[PDB]
Amino acid sequence: QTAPEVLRQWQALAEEVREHQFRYYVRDAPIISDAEFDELLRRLEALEEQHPELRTPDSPTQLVGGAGFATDFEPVDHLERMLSLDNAFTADELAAWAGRIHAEVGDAAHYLCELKIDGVALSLVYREGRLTRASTRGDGRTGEDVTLNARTIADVPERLTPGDDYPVPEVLEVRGEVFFRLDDFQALNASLVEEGKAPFANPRNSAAGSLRQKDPAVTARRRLRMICHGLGHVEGFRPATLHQAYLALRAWGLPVSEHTTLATDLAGVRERIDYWGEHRHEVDHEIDGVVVKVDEVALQRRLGSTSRAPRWAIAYKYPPE
Ligand SMILES: Nc1ncnc2c1ncn2[C@@H]1O[C@H](COP(=O)(O)O)[C@@H](O)[C@H]1O
Ligand SMILES: NC(=O)c1ccc[n+]([C@@H]2O[C@H](COP(=O)(O)O)[C@@H](O)[C@H]2O)c1
């Protein structure tokens, strides 16, 4: 065993160094000067000379000076199973879902109405306010590790911002959608064609492909965006409602949509659906529908979920744009 202070110092220094290596090489966006970084690395190298067992092929020093940053899409489990959503395509279907909800929990349920973004699902995990893992949906229990790629998304903060009202959770699994804005999708296609590459047929395909890059620097060069729309496993945070949960996401620095509204009953839900039916074209990214969710966490627990989806939510899908 190496002495505890030595090990502590090495770990801390190596992590700080690797982070700047990632920020400089992958993102082309350093956050400390070249001089500052150089002293940092010099120090890590000194520590390793004094204790050569610390020099490993994985060290930011011994091996990885050019880069060692590749995504391999290895399977990684979600903390809580990621489900899909049941759909409704007609007024009748939606009313039937509402009725079922009424029969189980009466008039105690309110409905959060969110815009359904037609992108790529991404699950992020923050441990003690720090981003540790990001993965794809996969089969729901297990997805693919695209942590490095997710680290290049501007909207995804590496660290959560501490706030008076909302303390940083011990563990936070937050779900969101990754997408391109329409103008950015066109721009990307033009750039791809300029290099002799095939363009993407649609923004969803384009987001998926941009996200899933073995080399995260490719992802860093593209304007991916992310909007959080849900919660998985959480520790140190017990929001009464989804809407209140979104306020904490905001305080912490996570990206959330400004188009969400809280309806009190089905008439309110119906109004939002009719409204976005008329105005979804004005949003700068693709919206295929409206997701209706029982807002009260306790009611969500009661209603539960099936193996494939929540009973407490439903996606009202429009006709193709
Ligand atoms: N606001 C949203 N809330 C929940 N899920 C959303 C939202 N927007 C997009 N989605 C995605 O919609 C997926 C289910 O969609 P679908 O299979 O088309 O019915 C989710 O699993 C999410 O990844
Ligand atoms: N400002 C930075 O964060 C940063 C990080 C990594 C490398 N670099 C620059 O690139 C070279 C350093 O060696 P590495 O190639 O591991 O990073 C030096 O020119 C260094 O200043 C800068």
Image: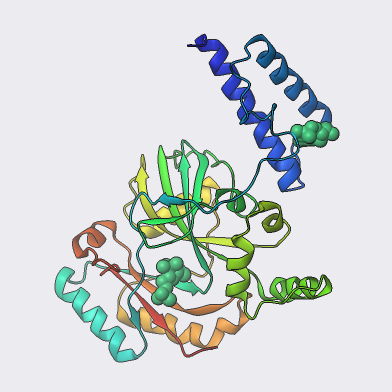
Of residues 104 and 80, the one nearer the viewer is 80
Q: Residue 261, can we see it?
A: no
Q: Residue 31, can we see it?
A: yes
- Residue 321 coordinates in the image, percent (x, y): 55, 88
Image quarter for residue 32?
A: top right
Of residues 172 and 132, the one nearer the viewer is 132
Q: Does 304 sit left or right of 112 as displayed?
A: left
- Residue 308 coordinates in the image, percent (x, y): 29, 68
Vertical arrangement, residue 230 with respect to residue 92, above or below: above
Q: Does 46 sit left or right of 120 as displayed?
A: right
- Residue 28 coordinates in the image, percent (x, y): 77, 47
Image quarter for residue 101?
A: bottom left
Of residues 254 and 194, the one nearer the viewer is 194
Vertical arrangement, residue 219 with respect to residue 18, above or below: below
Q: Does 223 sit left or right of 125 as displayed?
A: right
Residue found at x 52% / y 74%: 118
Of residues 191 and 253, the one nearer the viewer is 191
Residue found at x 58% / y 53%: 150
- Residue 143 coordinates in the image, percent (x, y): 43, 57
Quadrant position of ligand 1? bottom left
Q: Residue furthest left?
A: 103
Vertical arrangement, residue 240 with respect to residue 24, above or below: below
